[PDB]
Image (cartoon, rainbow, N blue to C red; front, side):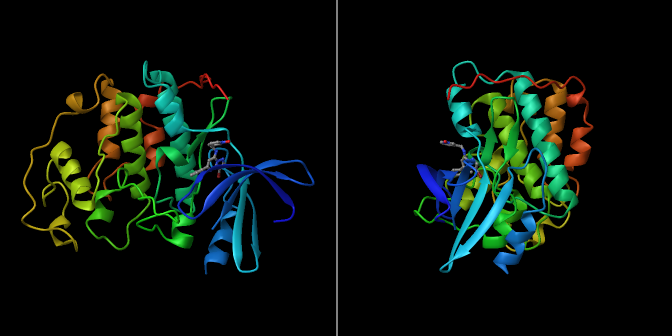
Length: 287
Ligand SMILES: Cc1ccccc1-c1cc(NCc2ccc[n+]([O-])c2)n2ncc(Br)c2n1
């Protein structure tokens, strides 16, 4: 750690404080995060793609663990808050979604999951890129109920199979999260802002209908499924994400399928007609 000068605290992550720092040698500006786990993290050093924030190095000293990452100036949460009045233009939402799906397709091809996608770990630069931060850390360290600072780990983007107690969930959990984020960029409001596991589950059911054996074979057997869940009818997507066009609503509906085996994959999503006219606009960033 003596090789880094901390510039400023840039937030509190799931696992510890996150700092903007400078390599006392190369002058490189990085994000420094204080955190079997060693081997898993070490492997993430090779999982490189332009839409995944680069893991530069791992430092383990005095039984302390520090991860050094490529630095980006802003997160999607702050960008959405700043874009609240007029909303993020559809072409930029589309570019971001397209880029995030490329990041997921790459990681998923290596069987690596994120498991905790949310606007705070989607990072953007001045060039119109967006990247996924903290990919793979969940498997290495787990996803706690509260962060190191006791902050509640959000449930808003959590897939229903996780909430229903599936032990061996898949890459589909990241597609669900990203679908939730897509809807939030379009409407300017979180899709399912649950404040407990049951409220999260019931918010999903109110919008998508209570799942049953017809739409999700096997759901009634899952560990935390209860026959006493209320039965809500499914809403039309035209009501849920106006004024998104039919191509976007079609893709969203596929990213939010209940049955993880039938939920669209990142690779298939990239081929969806919604991306026929995709471009890469540049956002207006005020740093
Ligand atoms: C992903 C995450 C979760 C929680 C806290 C920080 C982070 C977080 C935030 C950023 N940059 C955005 C930012 C925000 C505020 C000030 N400055 O200078 C930059 N970065 N940049 C690379 C990583 Br890797 C990272 N992780």
